[PDB]
Structure formats: structure tokens, C-alpha cells
Image (cartoon, coloured by chain):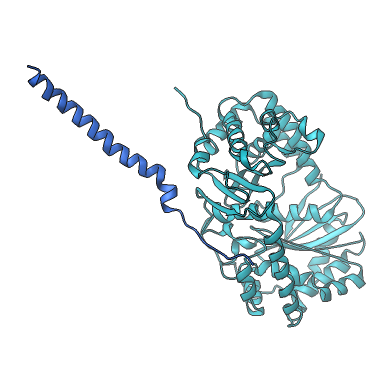
Amino acid sequence: AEVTQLSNGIVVATEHNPAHTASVGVVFGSGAANENPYNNGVSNLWKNIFLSKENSAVAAKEGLALSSNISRDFQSYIVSSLPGSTDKSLDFLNQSFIQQKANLLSSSNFEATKKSVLKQVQDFEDNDHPNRVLEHLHSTAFQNTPLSLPTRGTLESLENLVVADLESFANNHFLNSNAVVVGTGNIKHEDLVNSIESKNLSLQTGTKPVLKKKAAFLGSEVRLRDDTLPKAWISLAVEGEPVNSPNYFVAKLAAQIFGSYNAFEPASRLQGIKLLDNIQEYQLCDNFNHFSLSYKDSGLWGFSTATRNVTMIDDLIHFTLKQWNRLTISVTDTEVERAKSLLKLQLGQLYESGNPVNDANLLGAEVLIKGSKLSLGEAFKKIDAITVKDVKAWAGKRLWDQDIAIAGTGQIEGLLDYMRIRSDMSMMRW
Amino acid sequence: PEHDERKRLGLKTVIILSSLYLLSIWVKKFKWAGIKTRKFVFNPPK
């Protein structure tokens, strides 16, 4: 099991399981949610220069692996190496966030990284439709709020950024009270906490990052219609639950009740999902998948989907939303029990994979928000505890007759007016 | 002969229908709100 955590001058957290590699990295409690509409993508830039060819060749010689990740609530910089070279990692990390914080930010390296994330972010907005739509859902759901800013950053704010912005941001954000050093792999807790307590210093200690305005959900829609696309990718959700919420698991289980589906996989078709009987008669879509996205202050509960049956897009929506209606009035025991079993399974495949950087990105995440990590066992415990009465109470609060956020691109002519969709959030009664 | 009786029903009718009319205007606006306030932005594709 594991999971140790002790504060010194900073805050160190680890979880080691004798595997094959050891990964160490610093996770900062600030991501895109902390950017401004005009420096959007300042973090995708930091991630990209950290993984720069110059900076990568250094750690490479030493035999280290560089991995970074940008999110909404946080962002991280992680280094993987062999079990004993845990010190080798510490040197490179501390070299890149103390000494070399004058280098890397060197022109012709920044001007090159600037062109990299540009032909990158453009490439995404031009081809990764399903996720572009997923990112736009947040853009509209949370419009004019922290959570509404895209991680990769806008394509305009990106080209206006300069080394001054990178530094500026980095200073007010890459602090000590706003950072947590994470170690995952097989290195003991006392093997790192000590190796860290070696090199003293502080670097802007006593400063707290800037605060802001609590994210909010709003009933709205963005329709990125493009008749030239072969399909129609659409995403729809309601205001979901935030990390460390009484219903963090109830919500996650609900999404599992309808789960995900892929028309082309024989096994995906035989699933014990009631909605499946409706979608398959005329093949209302090539795939759909429900989620329960949780962030610091809010979340999004709903589903994403892709279809080529552009003439019957209203039926895909209708059947789906009417199935959701069930969660408030008629969801069954065997639907819940299945959900549990499948949630425990997929939740398990996440928290315990054969990748340390994965465990890292999940560890840093919780200790940054709840100052501790919840053990998979404790999880399974809370999950098995959920009853139908619980799933129903949640549905009546979060789903039944509530506003929704819609996003879509491609051939969405057939996607009906907000109000129609907004009306299927309930059902007639006497 | 229907006189008095007629003007009385007239009063009930005009009141009720008047209310239905006003109510209906207010209801129509609510449903149409999404479309009325709607906004469009154009970006000529490359």
C-alpha cells in the first residue's frame, strides 16, 4: 500500500513499490486555471522548454528520463531513472530549477520552442477534433472563469508570449508553498527526504501565489460546425463534482453505469448497458464515453461521442439523455453492482499501473489538493458502500432538470436547439 | 334577453383570455431567449 508524507521547508510525498525504475519530480499547485486570457499557454511553454533538445541531452547522458504534464489545477516536471540513481535525478532537477533558470530561457532555444508549441497547438486544433471539442466544452461550460482556459493555450496568446512572461509567471507561481516534491518507483521515503534535506536554501520563501475568482458552471453551448468533416463529434455535460467531495465516487460510478462504447468492437456491443439496445438498431454512433471530470472548484459530468449518422443525431441525444433520466427515478441494483465492479477495476488499472510517472502525476495531484492520498483500499471501501438511494439522491441534485453545456464540431446540422436538448433532462409526471 | 347574463360571461372571458395572452407573451420570450441572444463569429478558413 504505502503513501508517506512529511513537511520540512517544503513538502515531500512518496509511495514506493519495488518495481523496476524510480521516478522523482516536482509538482506545482498551479496550472492553466491560474493563467490569464492573454498569457494562456505559458505553462505549455514551460513544459516544452523543460523537455527541450538541449535540456534533454543533458539528462540523457546521465541516464535520466524527462516527463512533464500541464493540467488545469496543477502542472508537473518529473524525472525517471534506475532505482539507485535517485540522487542523479535530484541533481538534474535542482539544476534546472535553480542554476539553469537563466539558461533554457535563452533565445534561439525559446524562439525554437515557441515555434514548436505553435505548429503543435495549431496541429491539435486542426486535427484532434474529439479532444478539441472536449477542451471547448470547458471553454463554454466555465466561460469567464479559471477552468475555461485551455491547457495547451490559445493560438493567439501563444504567439504574443515572450521570455519576460515565462519568468514573470514562473516567479509568482513556481514557489515553495505551492509545490510538492514527489517520488514514485521503489526508492524509500527516508532515502529521498534525506537526499532533499541535504541541499539547503529556500528560494522566495514566505511568498504565496496570487488568488483569484472561484470557477463557475453556466448553461451554454459552442457549436463549431464544419460540414467538411466526415463525422460529427459532440460533447455534453452538467456541473459535476470537485475532488474531495462527499459524492466524488457516487458521480464516478454513475458515469460507469453508461460507461463507454465502441460500435466496432464485438465485445463492446455485448455490454450490460441498457442504452445499447437503442443505439445499435440504426447505429446512432461509432463510439461514446461517459466521464466524471473532477477539478479543484468544479467538474463536468456527461459524455463525449462521435457519429457518422448525421441524420439521426437527435435520436442519439434523446435516447442517451432519457437513459440518464433513469438515474433519478428507476436505476436498478444490478446496474449499480455492475458499476461498482467495473469502477473498482478501471480505477485499479489507473492507481496501479507499471509506470512510476503515472503514479507520480496522480500522487502529486491529491497531496496538492487534500494534503494526503486516498489508498485504493479505502476507495473500494467507499465504492462498495454506495446504494441505489445514494445514486438517486445525486441524480436528483446534479442531473434532473439542470442546465447543460454543449460542444460540437463537424456535421452538427442535425444537433438540435439547446432548449430541446435541455428539455430531455427530465420527464413528464402527474 | 340574454343581455345581463352575456355581459357577465363577457367579463369572465375577457379577464381570463387577457391573462392567458399576457402570460403567453412572457412564456414565449423565455423559450426564445436562447435564440434571441445568440451570437456568431466568423473566421475565414485557410
**Residue A175 seen in the current view:** no
Task: Give coordinates of residue A286: x percent, y percent.
Answer: 72, 41
Q: Which residue is drawn at 75% across and 82% down?
A: A108
Q: Residue furthest top?
A: B1
Task: Give coordinates of residue A75: x percent, y percent.
Answer: 70, 61
Lateral position of residue A313 relative to residue A103, left or right: left
Front one among A65 and A260: A260
Q: Quadrant of residue A190?
A: bottom right
Picture quarter with the C terminus of chain B: bottom right
Q: In which quarter of the image is residue A158?
A: bottom right
Q: Which residue is drawn at 59% across and 67% down?
A: A208
Q: Residue at x 80, y 66 (%)?
A: A196
Lateral position of residue B27 relative to residue A49, left or right: left
**Residue A360 seen in the current view:** yes
Task: Give coordinates of residue A128: x percent, y percent.
Answer: 71, 56
Front one among A375 and A68: A68
Lateral position of residue A77 relative to residue A143, left or right: right
The shade of chain A is: cyan
Picture quarter with the N terminus of chain B: top left
Position above or below: A222 against B45: above
Position above or below: A2 against A165: above
Colour blue belongs to chain: B
